Length: 130
Ligand SMILES: [Ca+2]
Ligand SMILES: [Mg+2]
Image (tube, rainbow, N blue to C red):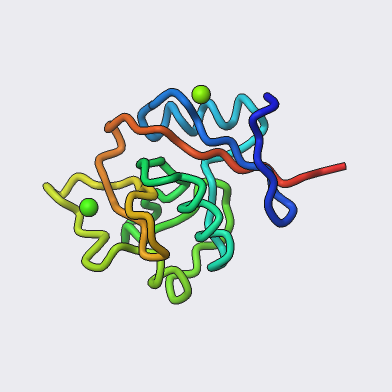
C-alpha cells in the first residue's frame, strides 16, 4: 500500500474498511504488520490526532488467566505507564464482554474496551526494516 504513514521508526495503516478485532489483526498480519501498540505519549498523540475523532481498533487485547491487558504485537504491556491512556473509567468491561481495545476519544485519554466482535476501522503498525 502507499497509504502508510511514518512516525519515529514505524509505519502505520489507518483502514478505510471496518472489521472485527481479529479480522482486523489478520488483515494487518497479511500486510506484514500487527494492530498497533502504543508506547509513548508522542505515539498516542500521533495516533489520536491522525484518527481525527473516529474509532479505530488498536492492538489491545486481554491475555492470561488474570485478563491483564496485552499488545498483540508482543510489545510487553506497561500497565503503569499506560494508565494515562485510558478514557477515565475505562476499561469498564461493559456487559462482562469487552476483551479488545480501541482508540475512541480524541485526547491522550483515548482508549476504550469494547466487544471484540464489534466492527470498527483499525490501525496497523510495522517497524521500518531495511
Ligand atoms: Ca468500555
Ligand atoms: Mg482498508
